[PDB]
Length: 536
Ligand SMILES: Nc1ncnc2c1ncn2[C@@H]1O[C@H](COP(=O)(O)O)[C@@H](O)[C@H]1O
Image 1 (cartoon, rainbow, N blue to C red):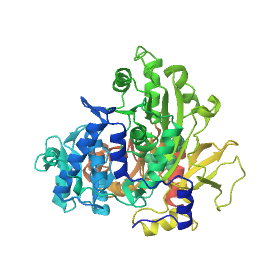
Image 2: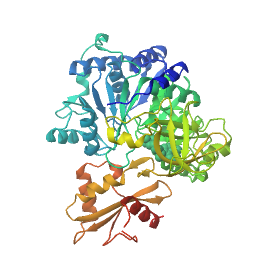
Image 3: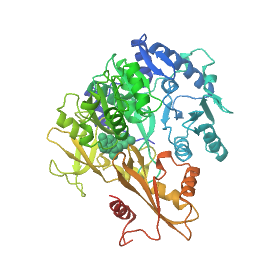
Image 4: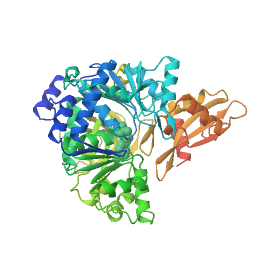
């Protein structure tokens, strides 16, 4: 159900040296041997060398094989920032199995979609995290007939398979499999726009290219200490350059259990972090904690680069990074579908603070077009289209959607409005896709509406983004009741019971007799645009 690059593009990318032929199977073996004695992972009271990570993943892989996981099987991995994540991911790569990455904030609705769409053989979860019981969630899927036949729990297993069961056998490399580098190595979730998010297949060759190139752009080496402040399996903290870039270069990955200034600054001080990645709301929290007193004492001198991305970072805030934190800002504008843009570490400050970077690859093609696919004069704002050696050509098993998201000649419609500077940098100026960006977490208005409409007291609903100085947008729901409106508390509870991801629950509920817009003779997309203007 994947879409391949055209043969003439694949040839171009291999001859250019982007696509090298290495697989993640090769990657695990080579990097853990090349850097064996160095420190690879710090988290949860654990300190693992590359050698130990190699040994642990080889044991795990043997136990997953004994469980029934074979080459090509999809396995949904929904783990917090704990060291078990990396040994689980490396193990799956050793078997030639495909991780299917879910984030900790995802819930029954999203996990059901991933398991059924990917036909997953297993689900790997923690017992509890941030007050949520993932064992109960897995049990709900089992009750509905939608759960993978294997459920593995990190922690107290309940009635499922404890992770420790997978460690019972000595390593057996006879069960490992090396896939083809052109094959999909894993699946990840898109941001989502009109409903259920599409699955994104990424290949060994194209993803490892973005990892290698990102490690070079970001000056990574064995002296790198990368703090995973964001959920590590998101594309940004996984590959831009993320923990894979760090592993590629032989550095240390430090896991932050949460991104609070107290927790993160304590790790930066203790472990001497040199680079980390955050979304704008976290960057603002860190800046405020240091500048306005709460954390001014912390020793952040080891921090060289603060990456900020996933959502728009205002120039005003960006200008605070070096004066307040003492480090170089790097803006990162990327997407799970491919294209990643970076400001360069030796760009002038005016470029670093006012742009969202330029693409990784010389073969990243950038088209900025008007509403009729005509290129806009250089400097003007238009729709961003892109094509390149690590941008996909189609979503996983999304035949009808792919016909709309990609041009006939293979350009991906990002849904972003951008303008290009003379030096190739891009400035993100708006959005055309129907998607609310809540401080880096993407919310589909139509998806939230559909669940709201399922409540028996609701007659109609419209979900829009309301401008917010810290998150960019919050999620506001306009609701028209049939007669008496439900309890705002009640409606939000009904949405949690539905299984919506935590960040998709609206911040604001406004019950109205009618939508406060003229000509309610307009499409639902235009309706949301007019409602959002009242809130901006
Ligand atoms: N630096 C940035 N500035 C503005 N928007 C961004 C930035 N980075 C990512 N995005 C948005 O996040 C989307 C990708 O979502 P994700 O797949 O979560 O990375 C992009 O298409 C943009 O809408």
